[PDB]
Amino acid sequence: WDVVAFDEVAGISFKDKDGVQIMKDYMASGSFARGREQMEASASMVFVGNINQSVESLVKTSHLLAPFPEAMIDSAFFDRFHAYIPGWEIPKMRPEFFTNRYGLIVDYLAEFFREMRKRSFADSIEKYFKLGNNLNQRDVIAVRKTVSGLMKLLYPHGQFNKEDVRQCLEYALQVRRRVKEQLKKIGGMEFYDVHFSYIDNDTLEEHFVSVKELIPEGPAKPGFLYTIGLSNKGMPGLYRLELQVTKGSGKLATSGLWNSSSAKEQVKIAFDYFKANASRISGGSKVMEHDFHLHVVELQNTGPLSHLALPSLVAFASGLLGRSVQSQMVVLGDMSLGGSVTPVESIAECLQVAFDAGAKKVALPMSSAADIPTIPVELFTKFQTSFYADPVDAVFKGLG
Amino acid sequence: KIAFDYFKANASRISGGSKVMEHDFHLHVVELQNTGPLSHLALPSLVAFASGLLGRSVQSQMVVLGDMSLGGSVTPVESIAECLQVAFDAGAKKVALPMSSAADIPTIPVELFTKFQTSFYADPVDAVFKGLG
Image: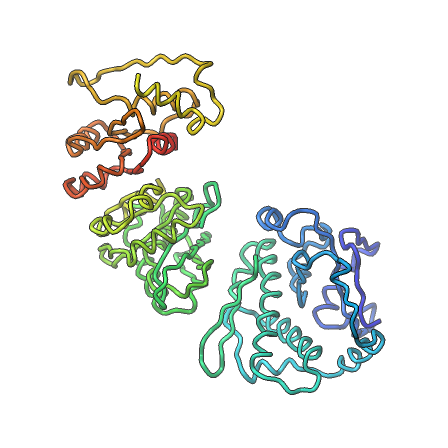
């Protein structure tokens, strides 16, 4: 058969305990070794599942592949999916959704697909684009297969424009990034590079594609915070910093910085400040015995930010102390290596971004005091101003 | 009495079901620095009734300043700076302020103002919501 589709995958059960790695190998290489001989197959595997809960509930409480059986909840096994079709956005079948017009023959369709199986169009993306730096080689393979398949359905004649490959590439990136988020959720740290992007070959613009899916009510895990900053295009934007701390030797890793030099130098200055002022801030905890990895995730698609030293230092202090930053916290402003604070750009705009439903308390720097009158009274009264003076006081206000 | 009347009037907007008519309140004023009688006490009284009726503990080491009218109009804090040094000497960590006292922020020394976590309530109901945390 050309396609095998496991219906109601929640009910799949295999008598042979060795089968799981057999499927792992079959999806990994297209061939499986049984006994002493290796058999190849061209059958495509589909997994059909029923979703019982709401999308938001499943996203917040679990991973979207929750209906999969416990025995099949594995990182490597889920890594082999070429796509995830989120059927919840597809409406339930209605007769008005059923056409009454002309259409090609189903047998004829299956035919044309079967002969199209012999051909390939995964190289078309190479003509107009390059893939971003946040996708591994498995991601490369998956996106190439998906774009080739969409090209096979829509453009069998081989004549195509750049807009077509844009649409196919972005669709593939979105469907694979959904899987990337699911694997990150189920596996913890190993799937952190989830920020899918593609660089245009001519314009050098890196377009970031995010899936369709400021603060949750409740105190977050230490090492997590939110900030608002003025991006390279000048619009205020919200970003989330996520710090992972492990027992190490003072090493620093960064991700989600849009591969921006400015963000890297700012966080490096912040790391230097934290190491220099570790004793007073941590009360004795040694930075030299812990490795920190900071991640930036952008929720508003506003663009990369340059000013990131102060929130990164706050995340460092929170993670090293293991005590949660205050709930609904928004950290504003930047800092110098000498501890001098810079006034927050776009006070009104930043507070408006913070006004987005959920956030209540904001730490403002002292230099922004002269900018208080520029704030409308109604907006200013809705927020608790944890007015700090220096980055040490900023950290203390952020941790309460 | 004005604070109690306002508390009766706005029970729904503050408590969400806790009925004033079914409960009796006893308010007791304690002087700790021998400073003398005070006049402006309506807004702190309202905060007290709201906290007691709801059983919600007030935020630790916060100081509520300002007074209110019967209709809910808030009055600016007279001599906010001296009250701030008093709070700093008293061990206070948070301050509750109305909008009108924000115009008095520039007259406040920056060092003292940096020591308190202001919430900047606007409405007396908003004053309750800020106080309850």
